[PDB]
Amino acid sequence: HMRVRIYPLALAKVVKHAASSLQREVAGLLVGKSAGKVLEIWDAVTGEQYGTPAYVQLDEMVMAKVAEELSKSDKNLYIVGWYHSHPGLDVFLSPTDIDTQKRYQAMFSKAVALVVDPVDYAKTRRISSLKFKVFQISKEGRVVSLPVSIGVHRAKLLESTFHALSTFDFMHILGE
Amino acid sequence: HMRVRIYPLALAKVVKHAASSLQREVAGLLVGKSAGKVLEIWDAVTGEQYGTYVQLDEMVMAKVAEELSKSDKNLYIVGWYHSHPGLDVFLSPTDIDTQKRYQAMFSKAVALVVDPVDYAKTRRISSLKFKVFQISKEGRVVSLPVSIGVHRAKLLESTFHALSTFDFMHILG
Ligand SMILES: [Zn+2]
Ligand SMILES: [Zn+2]
Image (cartoon, rainbow over all chains, first blue to last red; front, side, top):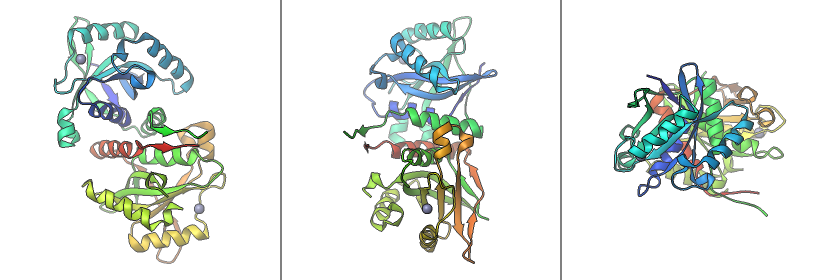
């Protein structure tokens, strides 16, 4: 099965997003690149930041805007999938999620769906309580859970952290 | 010489703060913990976030310390950072006096000095220009060996924490 490597700030952003809002399902886009046979996840962007607080995984206009912006980044990054939370429901793809993931794979064969259920992590504050999986649909149409590692290659760790920090939609007050 | 292990989000926050002010020196606090003989830097926080020359501000440092204390990640103030845009990376006479005062309070305290100009221009990691210093028993300024922290569990813990402390209401402009 394809290995997935997630750099730590991408995962932190997913988790913070999911755990921040336990009474609803949140979603966003995964940003990264292939590294030989491994799919690397460098960043995660919320639907909210692009104006879509629910179901941004289905929002083609947002995907095109994110893709156009990455067109400039010059780290050679692209959309690699989508994420969403399932608070209190555990981690799986629903029938609708499967259809969404099939469409993602049509546009990029290595696309993945990260599903997180942050409830236990919110309760214990231990990262070990996190429940998440990264899925693809197999060629036989089966949902498969992929092996996930944390990315630690030092140069890419630095680059990915600097990138993911730069895209975090921090709260701010503008000067006039 | 003491090894310094800096987790990547802490570095990134220092550099982002420094690169946001290319026409003036900025400063902040380093947060971390000792891991045997190694000093770990887990986070870097600005004075602004606590109301702040923050490296000299004992009221802020006490507030930062109190708050770190109540959370149980066993993190502490372990030094200070500041930028020298366009001037390269050294400790000035004034910085040396500041650093001596830090080491009086915590023997492993360090001074990170960053010159963000090349990084601001290229956005390449290879353009980073920074050093981490202590003052020796003889009064010499020692540049310490620096590694990037990659231990998987601490890398996650430090990243999740440093993101949490970044996410405040920034007053810009
Ligand atoms: Zn779902
Ligand atoms: Zn200085």
